[PDB]
Structures are given as structure tokens and as C-alpha cells.
Amino acid sequence: EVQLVESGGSLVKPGGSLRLSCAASGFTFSNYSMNWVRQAPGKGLEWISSISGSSRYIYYADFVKGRFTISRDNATNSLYLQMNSLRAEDTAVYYCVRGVIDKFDYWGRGTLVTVSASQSVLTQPASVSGSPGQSITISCAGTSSDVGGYNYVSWYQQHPGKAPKLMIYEDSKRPSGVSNRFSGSKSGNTASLTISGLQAEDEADYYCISYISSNTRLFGGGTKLAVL
Amino acid sequence: GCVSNLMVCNLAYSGKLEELKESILADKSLATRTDQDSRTALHWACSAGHTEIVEFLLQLGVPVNDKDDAGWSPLHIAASAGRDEIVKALLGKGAQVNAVNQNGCTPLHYAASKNRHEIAVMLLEGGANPDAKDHYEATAMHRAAAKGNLKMIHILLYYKASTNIQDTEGNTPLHLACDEERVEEAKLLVSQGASIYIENKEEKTPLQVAKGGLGLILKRMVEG
Image 1: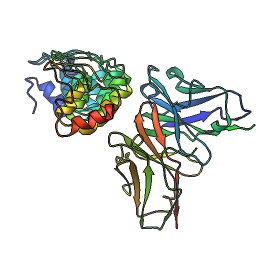
Image 2 (image 1 turned 45 degrees about the horizontal axis):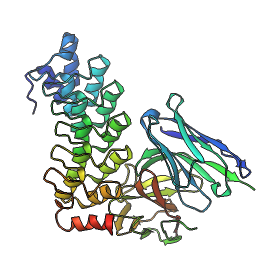
Image 3 (image 1 turned 30 degrees about the horizontal axis):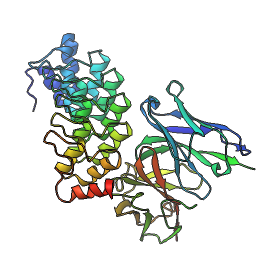
Image 4 (image 1 turned 90 degrees about the vertical axis):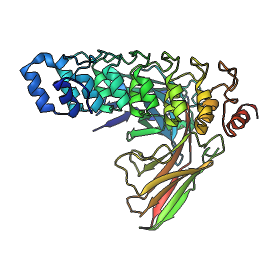
């Protein structure tokens, strides 16, 4: 079974410098691009950095600006993130994530980083009232620079204190093992996730991510689905 | 249907592992016996996508990089036919990701044109040259662009494939996307570096070979 275990998450005064680690197992680590994705309290899933299996190709989100540095050791199946000059906006749960392009298929439980001491680019509804058996839809809206017909939106499901799950990628395609009650679509600069025949196990948090390029992954602020 | 004149190659193609094991048990040399096209059981197992049979052959230590009479290696065959697990096994046993056939094609060319996404990622993670040009001076991006394989273009871009390599007719992948009126693919290419100004050997830019209103769509993007 594929496992990702992040560690190194602590509390640290602003200006401090952390180093996260991840132990990987259950797959051929060296053959996979790995990523770091962080999630601030109440905020969405912000991709940080990716590194190819061989370490040949490394990308960073724009905000990084040299402060973070990803690395890996295929020999010991471990991924690292060197974080310098920790601001308070850095406070988040940091996830180790396997995947390439829009397909973030495996996440760890994540490690919490607290810096002790402006909305999201994509727009989701805050709340969604559902009724067992019915059908609801969560929207993800951006400009023409954010959501287009030639790039992808992905949908991620998350239960309190659990590793985010990939429900939909490539706008509409869903991974094997995911219920067909989940579907996705897109019109213009807006993607929509839909669930039919709601369960109570369907109650969770839902996040959208628009893949634009290898260094640009836009995200929404998240949507809480309440199942009556 | 299998055209091999060899019984053993036919066993490999139709996935008869036990029968193949018995044959080879009776005569070890059959594992690497070449047919009329210099294909062995391995080539044929890759073609049909019989993973267990490839695994068996590999653990016997058969060569994994021998090319048939058309220059196709097992990796070429596995990638073209879309055999995910076999490509993985081959790459694991030292298959050459950048091997070329008599047409100058690498396994990536076929993955790209045939829309083998997992295989493409495998090849590229495995060190495949994305800008490798065949004897027509065409790249995987040319294939992806012409067929309208959006996801494949995204994959290639992540591994830093050039968008502006010109083939033997002087066409870039954008020329091809425009000619086949692959709208979203053409937009993507432009949005990520593909030049609308490069002329092919008929002195046409990609806008001048674009069909429908695609030329103006791309002109807008670049020039407003």
C-alpha cells in the first residue's frame, strides 16, 4: 500500500527556518514526480513545488521566490523541503503529494507548521446544503487567464484530519476507485463538480485546482458540503 | 493475427505462458530464436501485451534492446501498443528509452501519437529526449499537435519539449495543429511559446495554414 509520511512540522517564530521530510513506500519512488502542497487554515490547496524522479526538472509556485527548496533522495525514498525565513502566512498543513500535471493521486496525512509571532484566485461557494439522495453542484470560477478550454480543473475531497482525495482530474475524468456519483464539467471560465445520491460519508470539504502549466496551479478557497 | 513463422513467437503472442515455458524448458535457445523479421518471443509478447510472459522472459535474462528487421525494439513495440506494465518492466531492465528505428523514431514518438499518457510519463521520467527528431525531422510534439492530443501536449511541456522545432517541410507543431484545426491544442501551444510567425518551406506561417477562424483566434492571443 502506497504511503507518504510527512515530518518536521512544528511551531516556529517568524524568521525561523524549517525543513520538512517525507518517507515514501509502497511504490517505486524514483520513477515518480513528487510535490509539496500546503493548506492554510480555512484556505485552499496551494501547490508549492514539484521535482521529477531524477531531480532533473524542478518547479516552484511564484510566491516561493527562492525561500523554499525541494530535494529528494531516491536511495532512501525520501522527499525534502527546505524552508527559509518563515513568515506567518506560511502557517499551514504541508502535504507530500505524488503526481504529475493535474493528477495528484496520492497525499500524506500532512504535517502542521505554525508560525507563532487577498482571497483565492479561483472562486468557490463557501457552503453547500445537501439532502440525502438528492444532487448538488460546486462551482469553480476564474478569469479567462485562470480557467480555459485548453487546461484542467481537478477536484479534491477532504474529511477532517484526513489525507485529501482526488475525485476528479482533467475536468471530468475520475480515478479508479471513485464512485460514479461524482462528476465534473466545465463551461467557459467555470468548472463544476456534481454529486448525485448524497451520502453522509459524502459530507466533507471540497477544493478545486486549475492546472495551467508546470509552475502554475491556481486554487479555490474550498467548499463545505453539509449533508442534512 | 500473428505472422511469425515461429511456433514460440506465436505462443508468446497468444499468451500461452505454460506452453511457452514447456517449449523453452525443452530448448533454452527458443527464448531468443529469431523469426523471419528478427523478432523473438519478447517482441511478440510486447505486441500482444502479455505481461506475465514478458516478466518470465526478462528473468531468463534475454536481451531487452534487440531491434527487429524494421529497427523496432521491444520498448518501441510496448509503447506503441500501449502496454503500461511491460514498458515499466522493460525500463526497469535497462531498455534504451532513446533507441531509434529505421524511421528514426523513438518509443516516445509512438506513445505521443497514440496517446499513451502513462507510457509517455514513464519514458520521460526515464530520461527520454522530448526533442528527439525522426527522419522526417518531426518530434513527439508534432504528433501530439496533429492528432489533437491536449493532455499529451501538457505532458510534453512539463518535460520541457520545445514547441517550435520545424520538421522537414518546415512545419512546427503549431502548423500541424492549425492545419488539422485542433483548436484547444493550438491555443495551448501559443500560450506556452509556440510562434505564430515561423514560416514553413512554402513560406506560410501557422496562421496562413489555419482553418476556420483559428488564425484570428491565435492572432488575438499574441497581438490583441
